[PDB]
């Protein structure tokens, strides 16, 4: 009596920020690698937004960690943000995985990503609390429509998952479009803070739950599955954790190493 993935996979492989173990996160280089090379199921995208309102792929609110710039994304126009090197940081930080072609990798827009990988790819897209980037949900749904991904064929086939820590962001999307699959993201320590009534009211808009993997036991995974959730823990990079959680009966993981999870599905 347990819901499975919409993709027709028993275990789905969410490429966390693209192939971010091997390539600079949230770049074409990284998304190319996990989509085309490693054959991961999802392209996972974190949304920020520029000064002039463009949705972009970046994990932090600031450009500091992953570029040769400093400051918040919203303090850059798109033109200015496109001058930044979003790849050389990765060569410094992980020299065994370094590549000369990663130098001067660019921050991609959401529009560019959806264009590049097209309507047949699957996307796992993250929104914020509604007070950090007001309008971002409406912008996101509009960009999805433009790229033929809100077509309800595409939706029931798991081509779009929208994830957030924010209830209010997800509830907003559920009102504007009840067909888009929604994934509630859970903090470290937070899953245990939540009773059945809370899990029921989450369940009224989210099919998906995305806890920190270290909060998952066999007992609680089974409980969440009995409540009708698809469970996709984050971020699982080690093969021993991958196997352990798959045996709990999760439906997939967010991972920096998509090859490793797909090997565990096999082995
Ligand atoms: Zn994320």
Image (tube, rainbow, N blue to C red):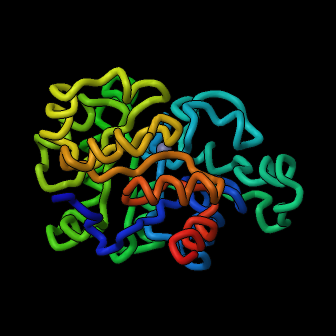
Residue 87 coordinates in the image, percent (x, y): 74, 54
Image check: 85 left or right of 127? Answer: right
Q: Quadrant of the C terminus?
A: bottom right
**Quick check: 25 above or below 258?**
above
Residue 91 coordinates in the image, percent (x, y): 84, 54
Question: Which residue occupies the foreground of this view, 7 or 171?
Answer: 7
| Rendered image quadrant of residue 115 | bottom left
Residue 23 coordinates in the image, percent (x, y): 70, 61
**Quick check: 238 above or below 72?**
below
**Quick check: 189 above or below 140?**
above
| Rendered image quadrant of residue 239 | bottom right
Number of on-image labels: 0
* Res 49 seen here: no
For the point 69% across and 55% down, which residue is it? 24
**Quick check: 244 above or below 147?**
above
* Res 177 seen here: yes
Residue 100 coordinates in the image, percent (x, y): 85, 66
Image check: 19 left or right of 163? Answer: right
For the point 57% across and 69% down, which residue is it? 264
Question: Which residue occupies the foreground of this view, 72 or 262?
Answer: 262
| Rendered image quadrant of residue 75 | top right
For the point 72% across and 62% down, which residue is it? 22
């Amino acid at each position: 009596q347990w819901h499975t993935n919409l993709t027709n996979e028993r275990f789905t492989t969410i490429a966390h920020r693209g192939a971010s173990g091997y390539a600079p996160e949230h770049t074409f280089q990284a998304y190319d690698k996990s989509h085309n090379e490693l054959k991961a199921s999802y392209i996972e995208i974190d949304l920020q937004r520029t000064k002039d309102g463009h949705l972009v792929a970046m994990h932090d609110e600031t450009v500091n960690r992953t570029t040769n710039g400093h400051g918040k994304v919203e303090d850059y126009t798109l033109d200015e943000l496109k001058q930044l090197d979003a790849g050389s940081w990765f060569n410094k930080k992980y020299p065994k995985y370094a590549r000369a072609s990663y130098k001067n990798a660019k921050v991609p827009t959401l529009d560019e990503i959806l264009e590049r990988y097209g309507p047949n790819a699957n996307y796992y897209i993250e929104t914020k609390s509604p007070d950090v980037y007001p309008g971002m949900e409406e912008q996101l749904l509009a960009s999805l429509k433009k790229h033929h991904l809100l077509n309800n064929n595409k939706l029931k086939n798991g081509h779009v998952m929208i994830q957030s820590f924010s209830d209010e962001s997800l509830k907003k999307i559920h009102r504007q479009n009840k067909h888009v699959p929604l994934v509630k993201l859970v903090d470290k320590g937070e899953l245990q803070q939540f009773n059945d009534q809370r899990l029921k009211e989450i369940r009224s808009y989210a099919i998906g739950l995305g806890p920190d993997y270290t909060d998952l036991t066999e007992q609680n995974t089974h409980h969440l599955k009995d409540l009708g959730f698809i469970v996709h823990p984050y971020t699982v990079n080690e093969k021993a954790d991958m196997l352990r959680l798959n045996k709990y009966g999760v439906d997939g993981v967010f991972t920096n190493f998509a090859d490793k999870y797909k090997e565990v599905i096999k082995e």
